[PDB]
Amino acid sequence: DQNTEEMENLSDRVSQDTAGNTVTNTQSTVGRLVGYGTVHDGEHPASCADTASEKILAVERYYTFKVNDWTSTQKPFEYIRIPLPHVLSGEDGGVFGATLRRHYLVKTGWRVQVQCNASQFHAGSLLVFMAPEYPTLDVFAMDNRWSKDNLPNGTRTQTNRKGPFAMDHQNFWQWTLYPHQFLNLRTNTTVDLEVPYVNIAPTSSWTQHASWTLVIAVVAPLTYSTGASTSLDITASIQPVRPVFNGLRHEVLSRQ
Amino acid sequence: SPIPVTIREHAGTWYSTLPDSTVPIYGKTPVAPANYMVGEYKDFLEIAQIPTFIGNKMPNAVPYIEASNTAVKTQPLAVYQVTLSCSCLANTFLAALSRNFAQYRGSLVYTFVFTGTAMMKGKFLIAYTPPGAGKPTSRDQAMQATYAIWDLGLNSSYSFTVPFISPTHFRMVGTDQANITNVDGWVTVWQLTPLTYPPGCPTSAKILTMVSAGKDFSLKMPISPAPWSPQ
Amino acid sequence: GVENAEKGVTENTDATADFVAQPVYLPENQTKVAFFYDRSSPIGRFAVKSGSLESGFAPFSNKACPNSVILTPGPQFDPAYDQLRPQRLTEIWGNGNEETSEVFPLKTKQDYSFCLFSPFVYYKCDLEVTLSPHTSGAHGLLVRWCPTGTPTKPTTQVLHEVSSLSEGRTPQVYSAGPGTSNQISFVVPYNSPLSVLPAVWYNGHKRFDNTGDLGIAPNSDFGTLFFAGTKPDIKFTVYLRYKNMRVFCPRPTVFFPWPTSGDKIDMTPRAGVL
Amino acid sequence: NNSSSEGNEGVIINNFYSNQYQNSIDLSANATGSDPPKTYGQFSNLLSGAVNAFSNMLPLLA
C-alpha cells in the first residue's frame, strides 16, 4: 500500500511541479493533499464591479525560503506559523508582493511544499497543516522561533484568573482535522498541500486579515545517534494558486 | 368537536413588523375614485436615480465647488468619502433614502455641472481611490486609481460613477466608527490643466455638484435613523 | 490494516478488513449538524431598568444582568462595565477575578454549549430568540431588535411618555397583559454583510488602520437587542436556537482536562479532583 | 430544511407564513455580473422635442 523500493528514494515517488520559471522536484513523495477536495478556479469575485488583474505569469510561481532548523531540543506540539499572504507581501514576494500592495483586494489559494531531509539513521516526525483563521501574531509575521505558547486554551487577559478559555484556543490534539500531511523522516523528505480560497466574503482585503496560516509543528521529537546530522533545517516552497487581484490604487508606503 | 389547541408560550405578544392582518371594523366602505391621478412611484429605487445636491464648504454649504486659474497638484478641489454617511451627502435623497436602510450595494454616480463662461476652458481629473493606503495626497497619487479626464466644451456636465469595489456583497449604510465594512475610499477632484480665459472674462467658475444612485444600486433591511432635529 | 498515514488520508475500515466479521450499520439522522443545533440554549440572565416603559433608555445592569444583548453565541459583556453598553469579548470571564474566586457561574454572556462544541471555522443560520421571565405572575416586556450594523443607541426619547425603545420603524415587540403566558418568541433573519460568519476566531482587525486586536470581525453578530419593561425586579433568560445551520471547514474543539485522578470519566466538573 | 440535512421540525401542516417570510432568501451571485432590470417602475419625467425634423422649413441657416 506504498509504491515500490528502498535505501534510496524510488519510482512513483518521483514527482515534479512546474509553476512558471520555477519547478519543484522531490524523489520521496507521498502525495499531494488537495485540501477540501477543491482547487481555486480563479473566478472573479461577484462583489466587485472592477474587472480584475488576473492570469499574470510572473506571479503564479513558487517562492522558496527557509522556515527554521529542527533540533533534538524541540518538545512535541511546538510550532511555527507562516501567515499567507503577508509572508509574500514584501521583497521575497516578487511581482506578487509588488502587485499586491497596489491592489485593495486579493482572492487566491495556496500550493505549498515543505522540505526536510535527514537520513535512514534519524528518527522524528513533523506535522504540516494549513488552517483558515488560525490565530497568528498581530503584525501577521512568520514565527521567529518555535514555541508552545498559548496552546490549548488561548491567550486571556492577564487579569482573567478563572476565565475558562479565550477564542484563540487551539486543541492541538485535534490538529489533524485541518488539511495536513506528516513529514516522517523514515518515509519522506517532502510534504505537498493545496487549499482553495475560503473566506467570510467573496474576496479578501488582505492587508488587514490573514485568512490562512501554514503551520509546521513537531509531533515526534528528533532522535539520532552520534555521528549523524545534528540539526535539520526546514525550507518551504510557496505558490499562490490563480490569484485574482482587484481594487487597483497606490502603494507608497502604505500599511502593509 | 370544540377543537383541541396547544397554546404557544409567546401568546399575547404584539409584533410591530408582523406579516399579517388584524380585525376590520368598517367593511364594505367604497373609496372615492382617484383614477385621474398621475405621478405615482412604487419603488424608492425609482426616484433614487435623480441627482440632488452635494454640500460643499459644509457647514456653510454651497451646491458647487470652485475652479481656479491654477492647477496645483498637491491641492485637490474637492475630496468626498465614499460613504453614504458623509457630511457632504447628508441632504441628498440618496443619503436621505439610504439612511432608512441597513446595507447598500452598487454604483454611486457623481454628476458635475460646469457653470462658468462659454469663453472659458479647463480640464479636471476625477478619481475614486479604494481603501488600504490612505487618501491620495497629490493628483499624481490619485491618477493611480480609477479616474476620468473631463474636458470643458459644448457639453456642460460630466457624470462620474464609482465602481462598487468591495470584499462584501453589500456595505453598511451608516458610518459610525469606520470599519472594513463601512467605508470604501474617496473621491477627489483636481485640475489637470488650469481654467483658461480670454480678456473680458471672470477668472474663476462654479461647478454644480449632484449625486444619485446608478442602475446597479440596491438597498435592503428597512430600519430607522437616530432621531434628529434640523434645529 | 497496513496504512501510510503520512498522506493526510487514511482509509475507512470496519471489523471486516483484518478479521472474520461483518458490518454493523443502523441508520440514524440525529448527527446531522442542522438537527443538532435546532435545539434552544441559554446565553444568560437579563434585566430591565425602572420606568423604562415610559422614559429614555440608558445602558444598565442589575447584577451583571443588563438591559441589552448582542445576538451572538460568543462571549460578550465584561463585568467591569456592567453599566456600559455590552461589547463582545474574545475571552470568557468567570465569576471572580482572583485565585480563590470560582470559574462558575460565569459573568460574561455566551453560548457555553456552543462555545464548547463549535467544530467549524465558519457558519450561516437564522436565529430564533426566546425571552423567559422568571416570574409566573404578570410581566411586561418591550423589545427592540436592531439589525447588526445599524443604530444601536436608542437613547433619545422623541414622544413624551413613550419609551425611547418604542420609537421608529425598527422592529419592536411587546407583551404585557394579565392573560399572557409571560414569554416571548420570534425568529430573526441573517443580516450580516458577511457571506458566512466566523464561529470561533477571525484573524484580522477591525479596520484599514490594522489598529490591533484581532479576533472578531466587524458586524458579525445577528443584531443588538434592547429591553424595557414593567416588572423590574424580575430577570429573564435569553435562549438562542439556530435555524437552518450550515457549517464550513472542520477545526478543533475545546480542551478537556486530564483526569489527575484515574482512567475514565464521569460527572465532578472544573476543579481538581471529583 | 436544510444545513445539513434537515433540523427539528415535524409538522404536518404547511407553514402559515411563506418561506420568503419565515426564512432568509438564499441568493446566488454570478462571478460575471447581473444586468439590472432596464426600468425599476413606470415613473419618469420626459423630454420632448429632445430632437428635430419638421418645422418652418430649412430657412435654418446651416
Image (cartoon, coloured by chain):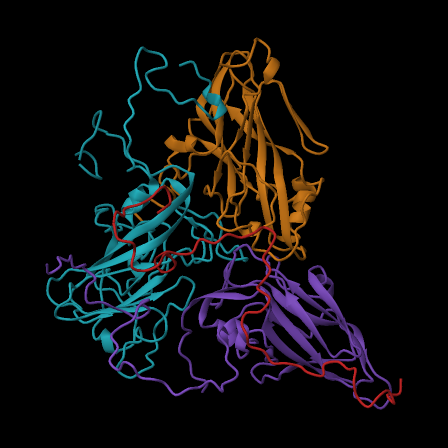
Percent position (x, y) of residue A59?
Answer: 68, 41
Q: Is residue B202 left or right of residue A254?
A: right
How many tags in the picture? 0
Drawn colour of chain B? purple
Percent position (x, y) of residue D26?
Answer: 44, 53
Q: Nearer the viewer, residue A230 or D24?
A: D24
Q: Quadrant of residue B228?
A: bottom left
Residue C72's place in the image compared with B201, above or below, is above
Percent position (x, y) of residue A99?
Answer: 68, 48
Residue C25's place in the image compared with B40, above or below, is above
Drawn colour of chain C? cyan
Drawn colour of chain D? red
Q: Nearer the viewer, residue B215 or C194?
A: B215
Q: Residue furthest right?
A: D62
Q: Quadrant of the C terminus of chain B?
A: bottom left
Q: Is residue C130 left or right of residue C177?
A: right
Q: Is residue A162 visible?
A: no
Q: Nearer the viewer, residue A156 or C175?
A: C175
Percent position (x, y) of residue C263?
Answer: 22, 24
Q: Quadrant of the N terminus of chain B?
A: bottom left
Drawn colour of chain A? orange
Q: Is residue C177 visible?
A: yes
Residue B150's place in the image compared with A22, above or below, is below
